[PDB]
């Protein structure tokens, strides 16, 4: 039976894929096989997606949009989650520390095309700090705690559990949750390569359907923690904190939410974003039953 390979990073934004996998194991005869392929950074994951070594992936929405603007055959079918993003600073730092008086502040981000960059820029404006006084440095999420503890950066923005890990692993302080900066900003989405939708629609629909059911199971916090402790190289305390600030449920990619990201990408001249109908294929998730 048809194997679907889906790529991910071990962050809460991809945890609904783990739940989907667990649910699929409960059928006597599942309609497809789900292979979850792990990556440590975003560029490696996108290369596997673009070369077809994986059939889909949970990925940064801006990164996927840029790839789409560059001719990618992918389509976003659902959100991976709601919230679950943080902005970390060095130990004992206060938001009032930031000013226009001295040297520039250095922030780690997972990729230049990320909601993390947008969150930080919005926080910069809310703090009335001049443009260019925050400098951004791309790095893998797992590398951020060490970069922070060893003062190569002032702070960072990333999906949990990499903020909670910063607090545990040495010295990091949670300055802000994404929620406090841009309420319900979309971050990661489940994207599928176009051929799955065109050529294996029954399998694609079955997969999104299991994914949809899983999304609602994940509202129960005990479950989201249990799913993650199983799959991720993190302790239960780090993952309880991580799960507490992430939500799932209705994972529809809504036009309004998508439009917010396009506005922000356009506003920072990142790239010209693709229209909703060219990037998003919301039929699979809408037709899938909640039950
Ligand atoms: Zn991330
Ligand atoms: Zn994300």
Image: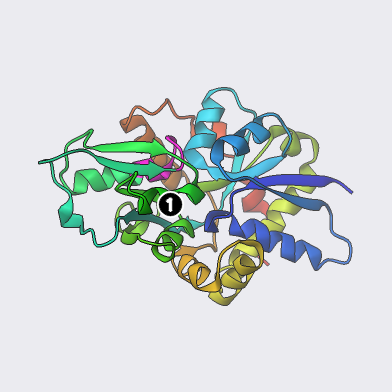
Tell me where residue 80 appears, x and y as whole percent: 56, 53
Does the magenta-highlighted stretch encompass residue 111? yes
Vertical arrangement, residue 68 with respect to residue 7, above or below: above
Find numbered disc 1 in the image and state the secondary structure of the residue it sits on: helix
| Lateral position of residue 125 relative to residue 284, left or right | left
Tell me where residue 275 appears, x and y as whole percent: 48, 31
Q: Quadrant of residue 197?
A: top right
Asked if residue 158 shows in the view, the reply is no
Residue extent of the magenta highlight:
110-118
The residue furthest front is 150
Tell me where residue 66 appears, x and y as whole percent: 50, 29
Which residue is rendered at x = 41% and y = 44% of the image?
A: 115
| Lateral position of residue 137 relative to residue 213, left or right | left
To which residue does mark 1 refer? Answer: 146
Does the magenta-highlighted stretch encompass residue 153? no
Which residue is rendered at x = 15% and y = 44% of the image?
A: 128
């Amino acid at each position: 039976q048809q194997v679907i390979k889906i790529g991910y990073l071990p962050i809460t934004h991809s945890a609904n894929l783990m739940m989907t996998k667990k649910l699929l194991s409960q059928y006597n005869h599942p309609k497809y096989k789900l292979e979850l392929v792990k990556f440590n950074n975003w560029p490696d994951l996108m290369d596997a997606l673009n070369s077809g070594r994986i059939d889909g992936a949970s990925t940064l929405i801006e990164l996927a949009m840029k790839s789409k603007q560059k001719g990618s055959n992918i389509k976003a079918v659902a959100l991976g989650h709601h919230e679950g993003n943080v902005i970390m600073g060095q130990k004992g730092m206060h938001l009032n520390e930031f000013n226009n008086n001295g040297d520039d502040y250095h922030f780690g981000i997972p990729h230049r095309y990320s909601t993390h960059y947008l969150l930080l820029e919005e926080l910069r404006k809310q703090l009335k700090i001049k443009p260019g006084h925050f400098s951004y440095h791309e790095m893998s999420p797992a590398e951020m705690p060490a970069a922070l503890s060893e003062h190569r950066i002032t702070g960072y923005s990333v999906a949990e559990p990499f903020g909670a890990l910063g607090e545990k692993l040495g010295k990091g302080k949670t300055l802000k949750h994404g929620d406090d900066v841009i309420p319900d900003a979309y971050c990661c989405v489940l994207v599928l390569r176009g051929e799955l939708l065109d050529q294996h629609k029954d399998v694609a629909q079955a997969f999104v359907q299991d994914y949809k059911k899983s999304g609602f199971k994940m509202n129960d916090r005990k479950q989201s923690v249990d799913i993650m402790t199983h799959h991720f190289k993190q302790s239960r305390d780090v993952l309880t904190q991580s799960a507490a600030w992430t939500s799932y449920g209705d994972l529809t990619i809504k036009p309004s939410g998508y439009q917010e990201i396009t506005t922000l990408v356009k506003q920072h001249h990142l790239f010209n974003p693709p229209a909703y109908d060219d990037f998003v294929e919301p039929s699979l998730y809408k037709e899938a039953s909640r039950s």
